[PDB]
Image (cartoon, rainbow over all chains, first blue to last red; front, side, top):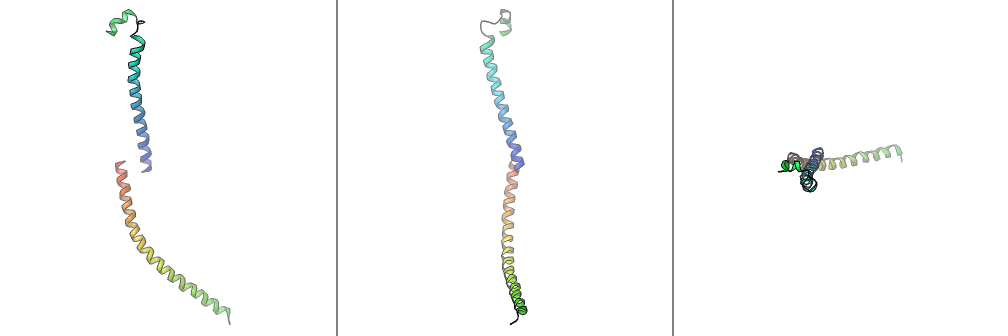
Length: 51
Length: 54
């Protein structure tokens, strides 16, 4: 029972880490779209790829 | 008058008193273990249920 408790604790830690990583990746992708390549520094030949 | 029969009767007192104490302790222990085994079986069933849920 203690061994399975340790296994469940490890799996729940992995689940929390994976969900946090997924949310962090989503917000990081949104912020990278918003703050890096949509600004005036975008090359005009990439204006159609963005479209 | 004689030690030799005196310590014979003293160790006889040892024998009878330890036998009486052993009788009482063994019978009380039989009843106590007979109920404690059922209590421990209930605890084992609870542990098995928690293990299945886990």
